[PDB]
Length: 586
Ligand SMILES: *[C@@H]1O[C@H](CO[C@@H]2O[C@@H](C)[C@@H](O)[C@@H](O)[C@@H]2O)[C@@H](O[C@@H]2O[C@H](CO)[C@@H](O)[C@H](O)[C@H]2NC(C)=O)[C@H](O)[C@H]1NC(C)=O
Ligand SMILES: O=C(CCC(O)(O)[C@H](Cc1ccccc1)NC(=O)c1ccccc1)N[C@@H](Cc1ccccc1)C(=O)O
Ligand SMILES: CC(=O)N[C@@H]1[C@@H](O)[C@H](O)[C@@H](CO)O[C@H]1O
Ligand SMILES: *[C@@H]1O[C@H](CO)[C@@H](O)[C@H](O)[C@H]1NC(C)=O
Ligand SMILES: [Cl-]
Ligand SMILES: [Cl-]
Ligand SMILES: [Zn+2]
Image (cartoon, rainbow, N blue to C red):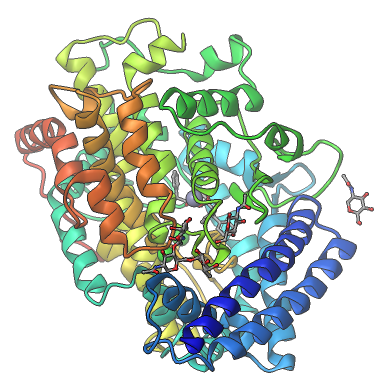
C-alpha cells in the first residue's frame, strides 16, 4: 500500500525534475552540435555533470525500491528503467574522462577534412559524399575513400580503446556484462541474436543476386582488370562512402535503359526546391495521413541546412526532443536531391514519434524499441519514392507503367533497401565483439574487414595497415550510437508498409502502393506510436500489422518481382553467386 504509494510518488517527482534537467541538457547539446566551439563544448561537458548528478540521485533512490513486489505495471517499468544509471554509474573521475572522450570523438569526426596538396579541402557533407555519389572514375573515388579514412578514421583510433574500457565499465556497474549486452537489452528480447540472424539469412538469396548483378555491371564499366566476377566488390565503387546504400550507381546498373528516366535532382533544383520545401513536403505527407503537423516553433529553431556563417557543425542528420512536449527540432545539412528528401522524411518520422508520445512520462518517451523509431519516417518515404508519387510532385514526366519501368523501380529501391541489410547487420556484430572483448584493439580493423567481406562481399581498394581504423570513419562509431536499430528498421518498415497499404485498401503488387492521404494508414501508426516505451514492443507490432513478430516476409513480397528477374538475368550470364575467391582484392 504505502510501498506502492512511495513508488508512485517517486515516479511523479522523477518526471517533473527529469523534464527540467533533460530539457536543459538538450539545450546545451544542441548549442554544441549547431556551433562547435570551445565555449559550447565547455558548457556541454558541464551540463554532463548536472544531468549525471540528477541521474545518480534518482537512480540511487530507484534501486532502493524492490520493483518485483510493486503491483502497478507502468510504475514498475519506469522504476526498473531509472535504476539504470548508464554513464552516471562511473566514479566522478571516470565519468569526466568518458564524457570528454565522447566529445572529442564526435568533434574529430564532424570537423575532419580531406585536402588536395596546395588546393581544396573537402568535408564529408556535402563534398566527399557528392564525389562518392557522382564520380565514375576509379582513382577519384579511391582518393576520397582512402582520404576520408586516413583523416577521420585514423584520428579516432587514439580514443577508441579507452572509450571501450569506460563504456564497458559503466555497463558492468549497471548490472550488464559489457556495453553490447546493455545495448541489446533495449529490445527486451532474449532471442534477439538468433531472431536477427534468421532475418538476415532470409534476405541472402536477394542480396547475393543483387550483389552478383551489380558486380557484373561494375565489371562492364570499370574493366575486367579491376573487377573479379567471382570475388568481393571494391568497397569504393557503390556510390556511397560506406557502400551501405547503392542507389547512386543506378545509372550503371539500369535493367532497362530504354525506359523513361526517373532522375529528380535537376527537376527539384529547376523547380526551386529548397531544404525548407523538402521538410514542408514531409510534414504535408504526415498530415495527409491524419497525423500531427510539426509546431510553428519547429520551423523557427531547426537547423535545416549547413550554416554559411562559418559555424562548424555536426552535419550528420538527427531529430531532437527537448522534453517539454512543445520544442522538437531537426539538425540536417540538407542538400536538394531525392536521397536527402528520403533522409528528411526519416528525420520527420522521429519528430512525429516525439509528438505522438509527448504526453507519457519522460521515462517512457521512446520507440517500442529503437527499431521502430527508425522505421516510421522510412515507411512514408517508401510511398514518396514511387514513380506515381514522384510524378505527382512534378519531379517526373510520367510514372510509367511498363513492366520494364517497373523492374527499373524495384532495382533502384533494392540498391538502397537490400544492399543495406548486410551493412546494417555487420556494424554491431563488430561492436558487440569489441565490447565483449573477443576483438582486441590490435585486431579492430582486420575484424572489421573480415565482416565486410563475409556479410557484404566487399574488399578494400587499397591494403589496410597498422594505424588504420576504418570503423572510425562511420559516424555511429565515434558518436557511440547503436546500429542494429537500422537493421531492424529496414525489415519492419516493409511490414508496416504492407500493413498500412492493406489498411488503405491497396490491391495488387505491394511496391505499387502509395499511402498518401490515407487516414486509415495514419491511424494504424498513431495508435502504436502513442504507446511510446510503455508496452513490450510485440504489442505495438501487432497493433500495426496484426501479428507480433519481426518478419522478412513483407520485404521479400515487396521485392519478389525483382528477385525473379535477377535470378533469370544472373543465370543467363552464368553468374556465380557469392565470392568464392573471397581472398581477392583489386
Ligand atoms: C498504473 O499507473 C498508471 C500511471 O498512473 C499515473 O502515474 C502515477 C505515477 C500517478 O501519478 C497516477 O495518479 C497516474 O494516473 C495508470 O495509467 C494511467 O491512467 C490514467 C487514468 O486512466 C491515464 O490518464 C494515464 O494516461 C495512464 N498512464 C499510463 C502510462 O498508462 C494505470 O491505470 C495504473 N494501473 C492500475 C491497474 O492501477
Ligand atoms: O544515421 C542515420 C540517420 C541519423 C539518425 O536520425 O538515425 C539519428 C542518429 C543519431 C545522432 C545523434 C545521436 C544519436 C543518434 N538518430 C536520431 O535522430 C534519433 C534516434 C532515436 C531517437 C530520436 C532520434 N541513418 C543511418 C541509416 C540510414 C537510414 C535511412 C536512410 C539512409 C541511412 C545512416 O545514415 O547510416
Ligand atoms: C501536457 C502535459 O501536461 N503532459 C503531461 C506530461 O508532461 C507528463 O510527463 C505526464 C505524466 O505522466 O502527464 C501529462 O499530462
Ligand atoms: C557560436 O557559439 C559561440 C560560443 O558561445 C558564440 O560566441 C556565438 O555567438 C555562436 N554563434 C551563433 C551562430 O550563435
Ligand atoms: Cl570501411
Ligand atoms: Cl539499437
Ligand atoms: Zn534515425
